[PDB]
Image (cartoon, rainbow over all chains, first blue to last red):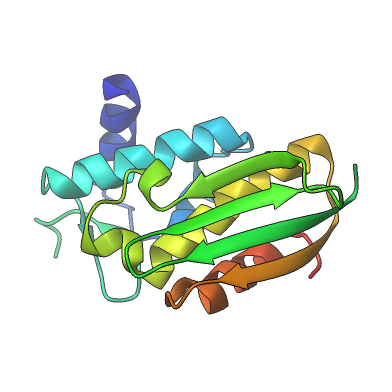
Length: 67
Length: 92
């Protein structure tokens, strides 16, 4: 769980990163298995609760500092 | 199996999505709570959407294509959750 959260956060920290929806994150991470998709959703919720990412009013995830 | 029902139970607290064969045997399921949403979030249609996707992507493994949908309860999820079944690829 933690290694996946770090990898997602690292990806969102990249300079080229723009705020993405869950589906756009699924596509960009090449998630094809339903269990990995479940991990992504759990990671997004946990990172959002920790305040390390923010969901916008258009259901896009972004880094707080960049917003 | 190809044909199946998507039972969407949208309450004010939670949106559950079970997908079954025509004989009502459960293929897969997901719920706002199962995706780690908590409190207000579970109610929201976005959570319903994501619950539908997760339930759907579990079904596509078993090899579904067409869905009949059944909706229960007064929650706000049903519109979002149904679109998400169409968006996941399964025809309604």
